[PDB]
Amino acid sequence: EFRPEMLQGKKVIVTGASKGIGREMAYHLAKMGAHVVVTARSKETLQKVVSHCLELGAASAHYIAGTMEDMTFAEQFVAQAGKLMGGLDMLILNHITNTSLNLFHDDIHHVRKSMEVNFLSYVVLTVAALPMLKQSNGSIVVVSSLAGKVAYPMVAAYSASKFALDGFFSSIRKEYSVSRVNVSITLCVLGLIDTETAMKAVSGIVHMQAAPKEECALEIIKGGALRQEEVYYDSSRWTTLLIRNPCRKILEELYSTSYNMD
Amino acid sequence: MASMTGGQQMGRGSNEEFRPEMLQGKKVIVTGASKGIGREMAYHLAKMGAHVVVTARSKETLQKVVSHCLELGAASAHYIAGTMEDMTFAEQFVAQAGKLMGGLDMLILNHITNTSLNLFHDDIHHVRKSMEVNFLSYVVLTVAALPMLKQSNGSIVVVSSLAGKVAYPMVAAYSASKFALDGFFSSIRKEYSVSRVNVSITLCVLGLIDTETAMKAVSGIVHMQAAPKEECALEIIKGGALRQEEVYYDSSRWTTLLIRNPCRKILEELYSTSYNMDRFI
Ligand SMILES: NC(=O)c1ccc[n+]([C@@H]2O[C@H](COP(=O)([O-])OP(=O)(O)OC[C@H]3O[C@@H](n4cnc5c(N)ncnc54)[C@H](OP(=O)(O)O)[C@@H]3O)[C@@H](O)[C@H]2O)c1
Ligand SMILES: NC(=O)c1ccc[n+]([C@@H]2O[C@H](COP(=O)([O-])OP(=O)(O)OC[C@H]3O[C@@H](n4cnc5c(N)ncnc54)[C@H](OP(=O)(O)O)[C@@H]3O)[C@@H](O)[C@H]2O)c1
Ligand SMILES: N#Cc1ncccc1CSc1nc(O)c(C#N)c2c1COCC2
Ligand SMILES: N#Cc1ncccc1CSc1nc(O)c(C#N)c2c1COCC2
Image 1 (cartoon, rainbow over the protein chains, first blue to last red):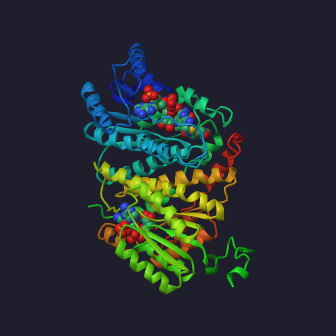
Image 2 (cartoon, rainbow over the protein chains, first blue to last red):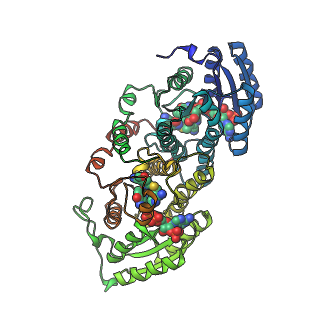
Image 3 (cartoon, rainbow over the protein chains, first blue to last red):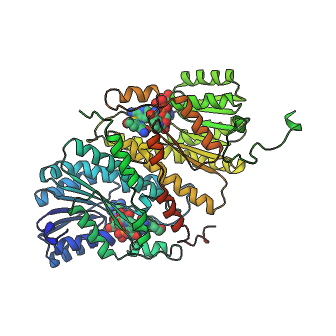
């Protein structure tokens, strides 16, 4: 059972926090009295988010602006965020590259950029954060999608990047378990959320009910605080009924007997 | 005689019962075909009388595969050597392979970057290279091949793994690349359905196979039963020929019982009615 006091005084990074779900997570963490470091490219918007976090009751709030297309920025950002807070308890990986609903034809540049921003930068940030998270027995929270568990047309590049996060982070979760690395990994499987970006992108194409961004942001934080392996959040009860894959969990357990990781 | 012959191999029961004559005279590309499963696929295709174009980096080993394909009965066999780390090579390779055969019926995407079993710590270079070679080059090859495959109502065959459907430790970079193939190719399969692109996409989910590379890599770390490479290679070809969406091949009857995900198929069908793609069609 989650309690908001679980975030009180915790040192948290939130990426993609100038708008949508990321901004809502920064606001919830501020209300809970966490220390926050927010990032995105928009310095001016991040200044406004930080000012608001301080008004809401954050223990401290800072922003560092930059692009996650730059792997050197991603690595340096974590070191600076850790230096500002004097450590790190939770790393919330939420940013994505700008995308739109379109059939795939020949835009390899978009496929590669989606893989670099939505996936590879999450790996770089994790590698940079791990020493601090090992010190605090901390948590990594990876924001994904229903399009990271099942297939959807018009989002091929985006879906490939979200599926990649599952393969990568679920593999390292198994490694951390056997290697006694006490850092939790929470994969958040979200359905359609009413962010301005998503609502504009889907307009006239997708008619699904969108879930509220404020509640979505809180469910992600709860999942991370509770060290849950997966969070599922969607407007539909049929989606919630069908999304889990118990057979995958059974197979992984059956194959666990076949290792010597010494 | 060929000019006085016509007809179709794919009649009643051809979506469920394979015959080697289904590959007779078909124009096929096999990547990663100098060794392991790819080499075995080139040999099966040769025995079936297909036209083959094989690729890998090793000019000398590909030379030997081509020579054996011709001995086995291939209608024609050629190789083009190069690295799939080079996206210009991948794009140009498909154009040259198509020119050699006078078209393309099946694109078998099988190559991977050299890897090993290790805990992940900080090798970002291996993560990026795995994504470039095992995933991005497959997309480049598909884009280059699609005009020819649309002309022949052809097939794309994507070689994946159980580590592309469930999580496994010690193969994080590799697993991320295989999961990426599922998300990408399964999304475009849905797009081709609505856009009336008659090109099938077969995702092959393979368990441990007795290739020299895999057997060396798992030695003393993974104690699992390995399935035979020759039978594996034939099951991949059969799935592609029958235009199956997925092929599952593993030594364990338990894996084959549990690997399918009916809930994912149900959800996708429920969401299939959730859109209006009329501006794209
Ligand atoms: N909205 C939905 O329906 C939905 C559904 C499922 C999952 N999700 C997941 O939820 C997360 C947030 O989605 P959202 O709808 O809140 O998106 P959003 O409102 O568009 O926000 C995207 C955030 O990422 C930042 N960003 C974009 N390019 C960047 C780059 N190169 N470097 C660093 N930051 C960058 C943006 O700020 P700047 O432009 O200032 O950099 C912004 O802060 C994503 O992981 C997404 O996949 C959303
Ligand atoms: N064996 C298994 O247990 C197993 C299990 C599940 C799935 N699979 C899948 O089966 C497929 C074949 O695996 P395998 O065991 O047969 O592999 P393998 O015997 O190691 O063969 C790898 C092939 O890819 C080529 N290759 C390597 N690097 C390349 C590069 N940069 N550019 C172009 N070609 C390159 C290799 O030749 P060069 O070095 O001469 O380029 C060789 O022809 C892979 O998709 C694998 O993921 C295998
Ligand atoms: N374009 C765009 C865009 N903008 C903001 C966030 C995500 C995106 C990517 S579109 C997208 N992203 C998802 O995660 C889901 C789910 N579940 C869905 C879509 C669109 O189709 C409905 C379901
Ligand atoms: N290293 C290596 C190497 N060499 C050849 C092919 C694949 C690889 C990558 S290791 C690898 N590849 C897979 O696809 C599976 C499955 N299922 C498994 C392993 C290793 O653990 C057992 C399961």
